[PDB]
Image (tube, rainbow, N blue to C red; front, top):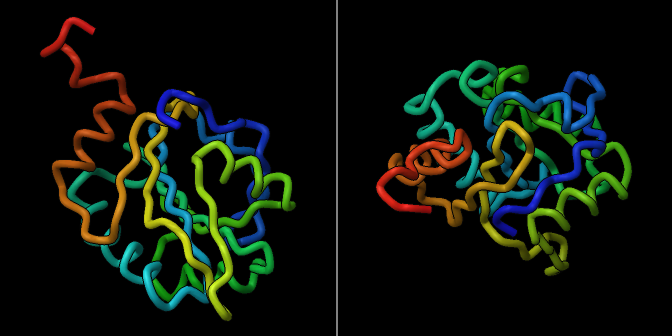
Length: 169
């Protein structure tokens, strides 16, 4: 929900096995991308689309964090490492992570109003990228798989508390 905060005590584990809390990423805007590692339908589209917009916007790990995270609780460190290498993701400025436990996962998906359901051997789920302020406040949602540059620029400006002086609020 726009304006609500993602809990900072959520524990994530990156594809190198480095454990951290979401609060540890405070201080820069955060771009969050829920996927799952065995997702052959929408998730390659989302990630490939991000790969083609992120370089326009700035440098991951400097201007903002990019966090691809898996929502499949069966995904292991092996799985996310495979995903990282698959898409040539650097793993530091742009991380691929899993939630440490199901509580970390629940909490994260609950905050961003994300729900998934079974469809045979895969999941039915929304296509969404979430943009957080440096304080973990949800500032924008960008839906779909066909991203445009302007929508990301606008989202990052909102994340930084910019782009608002055209209006009295």
